[PDB]
Image 1: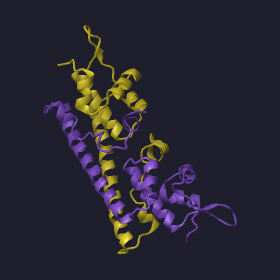
Image 2 (image 1 turned 90 degrees about the vertical axis):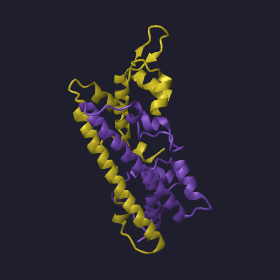
Image 3 (image 1 turned 90 degrees about the horizontal axis):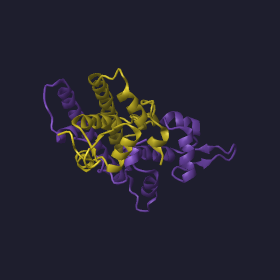
Image 4 (image 1 turned 45 degrees about the horizontal axis):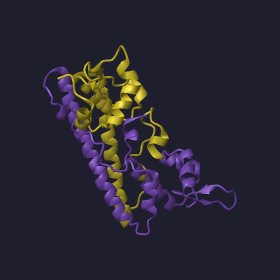
Length: 140
Length: 140
C-alpha cells in the first residue's frame, strides 16, 4: 500500500530514521502525514524516489544537487537513470584500476617488481566528480 | 631522490597542498624539512606511505584510524595491503551488485518487469564498514 511507516522504510532500506527525518526536513523526501495518527506515511512513489536518491549518494552527489535534479521541471527519470548508470560504471572501472595498482603494489613490497611514481598513483582520481569536496574525500 | 617538494607531490598524486599540509599538521604524513630553505621534502618512503593512506581513504577509513594503523608497533605492511585488497574487492562486488539493481530499475521504469521492494534496495550497504558515519555517507 501507500502507507509505509518510517520504521519499516528504515528497515527496508538500511537508511536510518535520523536520515529520513533530515530528508523530510530539507524537502528532499516529503511523505504525506496520516490523518489518524499524524505519522509520516511513505507511498510507493516515495520509495522509488528514495532509491534514486541512494544511487546519487553512492555517486557522491551532495543533497542540494540531488534535490535540484529531482525538482527540475525538465526531470526525466529514464534519462537520469541512464546517466547515473554511466557514472556508476565509471566508478566500478576506477575501482578495477585501483585494484590492479594494489596488486602491483603487493608485488612491489615483496621486491618482485619495481614501480614508477606514476604507476603507484594510477587509478586515484580526485577531480572526476566536480561536486566532490576534497575534505569529504580525503580528510576527517 | 628523497627531496620531493610539496607542489611536485601534489601534482603527482592529485592530492591538494591543503590536504598535505593537514596530514603534516595532524602527524599522519610528516616529511623532513630542508636544511637550506626550510621546505618540506618528501622521501620515497613518504610517497609510499601516502599511497597506502590513499587506499585507506578510498575504503572510507577516518584519518584517526589510518594513523593508528600506520603508527601501530605491530604494523605489517604486507598484511595490511592484503586486508585492504580484500576490502577493495568487496567494495567492487557491492558496486557490481548495485549496477545489476540499477539495470533492473531501468527495466522496471519501462514496464518490462516489476520489482519487489527488497530487490530495489539490493546492493545498498550502510553497515558493512563500522567506522563509517551515516552523515558522511548519506547527508550534506
